[PDB]
Length: 284
Ligand SMILES: OC1CN(C(c2ccccc2)c2ccccc2)C1
Image (cartoon, rainbow, N blue to C red; front, side, top):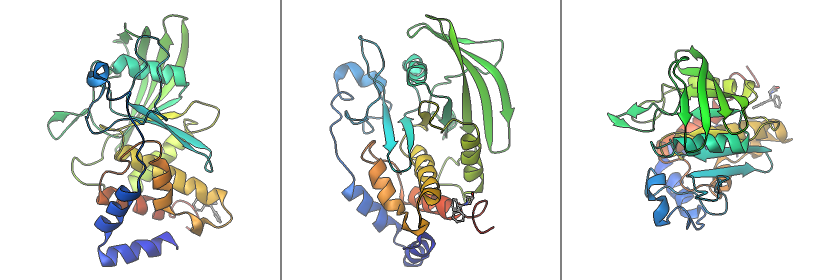
């Protein structure tokens, strides 16, 4: 069923809450035993948001391999994403270790450091060229190379250096800065523009490791980003795009991380983003 028609039918009936609860009820439940070990309590931002054991990212160290991060592998779309929480003061070194070990090219950030008067994630990247950051626990150095500030997003060039081998890589930081403190954006235009900028960079492409995507918990805004990307890509892949079922794509992604899309308003916004994905694509 063509999604703009499914969309108008749900809107006219005001049944967003009922669709959303059906998804919550059918979503996968897998064990998260490593996340709940007492040694890992200070590595988790939220007690109710954990990575599944089967899909968790492992740090390449013998001490403690744990980070709150999941590999989302979309087989038909041929895309992979790592979804993670906003780093904590004690996990900033783990975060950059993961970026290094997984060979990621891009980091996508969908939150501000402070929202609603509280801290949503650590200041994990340098704000001035001449004041670099050293992570002594993981032996990495991070330098700001350049910054491009636009109305709805900022793009940064960073240099990550493995101090053990003296190898360096360029990491692109894509920071969406205008998601509102409450609710979802009124138009998906600036979000879609942002997604197209990440794609243009090469960050989502198979010649690199998976993109790292985060918000505060790494399930809501982060879920919307990967759901919209996978949906529009599948429209160019299939002989009939009308066959792309956003609810079925979301349940597939929820096999790899719990809780993706946190509200009925985010579900509606993700439908809207994929639907309004038409404009600045096929037709006009
Ligand atoms: O290269 C441009 C992307 N356009 C496709 C497209 C359509 C919807 C969403 C993503 C992409 C397309 C056009 C006409 C027939 C079937 C698909 C053509």
